[PDB]
Amino acid sequence: ERQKVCLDIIYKMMPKLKPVELRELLNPVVEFVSHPSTTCREQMYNILMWIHDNYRDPESETDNDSQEIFKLAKDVLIQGLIDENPGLQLIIRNFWSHETRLPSNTLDRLLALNSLYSPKI
């Protein structure tokens, strides 16, 4: 419960931090991939979808953190397709399979599935 409320106070305060702070916060939240208590893990993934969608940086490259944390977020959000809980794994599957995160020509989707290799899976 402490960790779930912590992840809540870090989800609500998150669209105010600057990448310098979000970087130092992103370590012990992505440390939640090996967690029991699927609710805290769903909060982790649920802040990481935000961190992913609002940090894609569509060809800006202005900040090292604003692409390093996107690297780490991508790493842990593709590390969730193998989640040992249906539904939650289904949520991550739907997150990835929606338009504009994996394409749908089945050619560029094929070339894009390589981008989510991430050895860990």
Image (cartoon, rainbow, N blue to C red):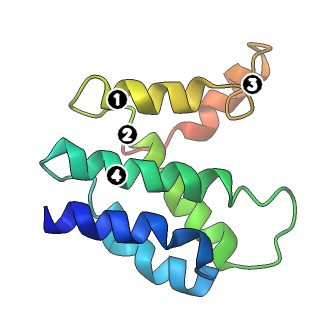
Circle 3 is placed at which residue position? 103
Specify the quadrant of the image occupied by residue 4.
Answer: bottom left
- Quarter of the picture containing the N terminus is bottom left
Q: CA distance from mark 4 to mark 3?
A: 26 Å
Q: CA distance from mark 4 to mark 1?
A: 13 Å
When the figure is inspected, residue 15 is found, relative to residue 46, above or below; the finding is below
Circle 4 is placed at which residue position? 43
Which comes sooner in the sequence, label 4 or label 1? 4
The residue depicted at 61 percent of the width and 28 percent of the height is 113
Circle 2 is placed at which residue position? 80
When the figure is inspected, residue 25 is found, relative to residue 80, above or below; the finding is below
**Which of the labelled discs sits on residue 89, or is there none?**
1
Give the label, 4 or 3, closer to the camera.
4
Which of 91/30 is in front?
A: 91
Q: Tell me the kind of residue under disc 2.
A: Gly
Q: Tell me the kind of residue under disc 4.
A: Gln
When the figure is inspected, residue 52 is found, relative to residue 19, above or below; the finding is above
Question: Mark 2 and 1 residues: CB-CB less than 8 Å, in contact?
Answer: yes
Question: Mark 3 and 2 residues: CB-CB less than 8 Å, in contact?
Answer: no
* Residue 97: x %, y % from top left: 59, 24
Q: Residue furthest top?
A: 106
The residue depicted at 51 percent of the width and 25 percent of the height is 94
Q: Tell me the kind of residue under disc 3.
A: Pro
Give the side of residue 97 with respect to residue 87, left or right.
right
